[PDB]
Image 1 (cartoon, rainbow, N blue to C red):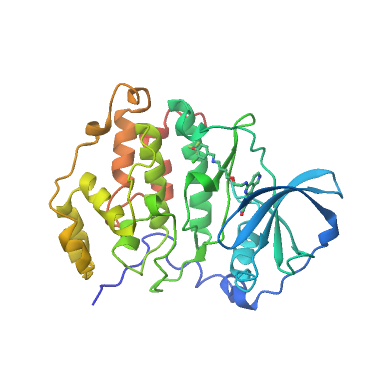
Image 2 (image 1 turned 180 degrees about the vertical axis):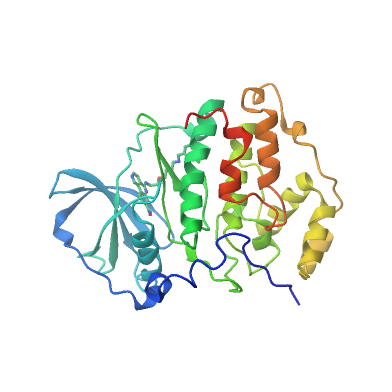
Length: 327
Ligand SMILES: NC(=O)c1ccc2c(c1)nc(NCCOCCCCNCc1ccc(OC(F)(F)F)c(Cl)c1)c1ccncc12
């Protein structure tokens, strides 16, 4: 059957931490006071929760409250433990409190507020310099969480908060985040369609931190080529075909042969035969100001089928693409 895989970095971080670190089920939640927070307005509703802008009346500061739906109320300890483990880390959203919502009777997570008043799609209107600057800021968060034995598993623009006025970035929504344990088989139903790595699409469960680096490459490709999303799958099956139309089918077949993966036979009639396209195929007069040989080389090194071949967050921070960014 499938060949095993393990991360090439931070492989054993959880084995050398005390069990209290990663055994989230044993964690005892310290509950705050729901009365400290006054809900102001609804910001959005997901499949398992709703988010509100709120005021912490003990300091008159804005906060964001995520109220869990009764269905998710049970599996909150994983997210809580990860948020507490990562608290204070570079560009990681701060969990300010955990309270029981008086209406839903479910857990409510209280987060640091980031000014989210930059309307439109700042995501598709940044300058070349600002793309590099913010990409480096995301990498500080990803190297931190990966160094802390945690995979985010939902890297996408909707989970990157930017206060453009103060050039502040936070990586949010650790609701799909997991502890990495070598040899552990994980659920492939993670990340959002357009940002799903090939490992998820071919049903390879023994993945690791490198899944976040594929998602990151999808964001970079979308920004530098002004193509939102870069890999525009109609469903999870077509998502792999869209990738194959860019990266080619040969490397895809080499990847599945290397890990002894059994490709879903539904792929036989839709994958076809494609050769790798050179990255300049995506360059045109409207995106040429964001494209550089450094950007293309960096992107090439993130968007690889083989999860063990992609740059790690630390290798990515060493890339020449970031030499122009003030440190
Ligand atoms: N943990 C929680 O559940 C959580 C924690 C905190 C918040 C939260 C959820 N949801 C909030 N609003 C609802 C979700 O609103 C998502 C808007 C995302 C906007 N991408 C902006 C953007 C712009 C440019 C980008 O490119 C780059 F290169 F990075 F520069 C990228 Cl990748 C992304 C919120 C608002 C204010 N302050 C804290 C929170």
